Image (cartoon, rainbow over all chains, first blue to last red; front, side, top):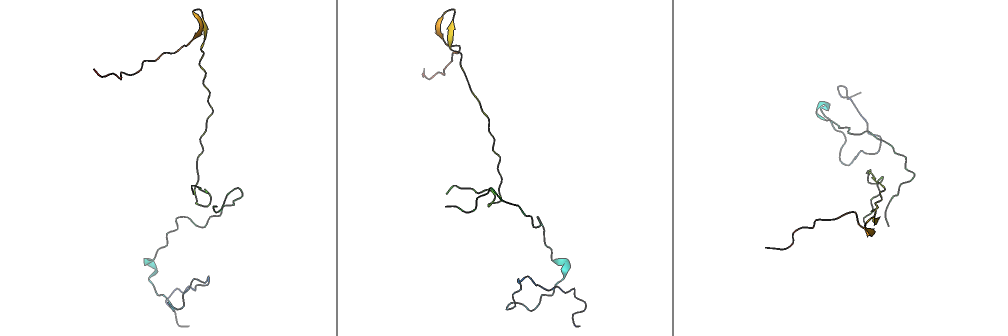
Length: 52
Length: 48
């Protein structure tokens, strides 16, 4: 088992681009994701979608 | 072309409304038949 000393994460949602990268190695303290609003669902029943 | 679908554009709106009526009591007085209860001062539109 080769990758000791990394926290390893595997992309499984089909976002990976295998023609561009084999792997990214990063300092995780220096990457931040701002979550202004996490995924919210609204049920629509009266609304209109599209035009013409 | 002016259509805003609020839910599809992630918008909301307020609708504000009121219902009003007006009546002027033009009526007979002790002076006679068709008397108006309001007068007006109109602006000076004549140059010196």
